Amino acid sequence: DPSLPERIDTFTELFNYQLAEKSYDIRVLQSNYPTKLLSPDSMLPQTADYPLKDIQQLYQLANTCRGKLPLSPLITEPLVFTRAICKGTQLTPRWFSRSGLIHPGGGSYAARYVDKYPELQDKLAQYMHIKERKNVQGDELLASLKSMNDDAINALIAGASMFIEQNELWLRRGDHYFVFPKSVWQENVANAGLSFKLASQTKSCFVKRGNICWDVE
């Protein structure tokens, strides 16, 4: 009687990938969304790189436009950003495409810049975190990315073999993810002799694939 890994393999071979209703090319995904613009952590204070003390001094240097900051190779880029805002220095779109994109206090440089200069919205939207971006008519990938919860988008960022997005199942095949609705995948789970729970629902995830904890029927 097949092992759990074997059934998962049997499970993915039940899908007709030519008939998937939605599919995305991972190369196109990477070229248009740098990982830092997808990571949920990017919206949070960047305490993995800067002490929370430095981040609060940056806000004070921002809010007052006076004040010194400790020096370091990395903080040089946020310092340029902060002073440019105070000095009224024009930062071009090229500057954002060449930057590390994420401000030390969480969020993107672009979103913060557009906050001061709201007319630059359309030029700098592509350098903003997806959580800072409005949905645009006919940008379904951005719509799909924005609707994912942390566990789902982190499985995407990890390039996981599969993951569940609400009621849709994302399956990786070559350079693409193929998206299938529950009306297709639920029966496939049963016909393969499987069951599953999400990583956030159970405490026991011994056979993990993306955000999915597989088990037998």
Image (cartoon, rainbow, N blue to C red):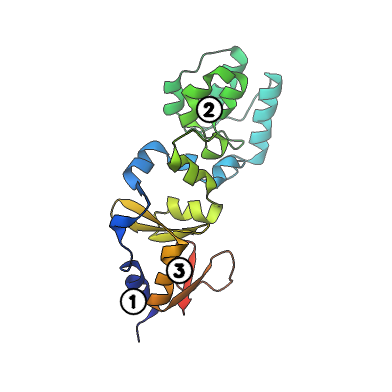
Comparing 111 with 19, the one in front is: 19
Between the residue at mark 3 and the residue at mark 1, the CA separation in whole angstroms equals: 18 Å
Q: Residue furthest front?
A: 183
User: Where is residue 103 shown, x and y percent of the image?
Assistant: 56, 33
Which residue does the image show at 61% across and 30% down from the upper left?
A: 70
Q: Residues at badges 3 and 2 in contact (C-beta under 8 Å)?
A: no
- Taking the spot 32% from the left edge, 44% from the top edge, the residue there is 27
- Tell me which numbered mark, 1 or 2, is placed earlier along the sequence: 1
Q: Which one is in front, 43 or 162?
A: 162
| Position of residue 122 measured from the top left corner of the image (x, y, whole percent) | 49, 23
Pointer 2 residue: 110
Amino acid bearing label 3? Gln
Q: Earlier in the sequence, mark 3 or mark 2?
A: 2
- The answer to whether residue 81 is visible is yes
Name the mark nearer the viewer: 3 or 1: 3
List x then y, in percent, for residue 215. Answer: 47, 77
Q: Which residue is mark 3?
A: 186
- Up-down: is 100 above or below 119? below
What residue is disc 1 on? 6
Say above or below: 26 vs 137: below
Question: Image point 61% across, 42% down: which residue?
Answer: 44
Query: In the structure shown, which secondary structural element does the residue marked by tag 3 occupy?
Result: helix
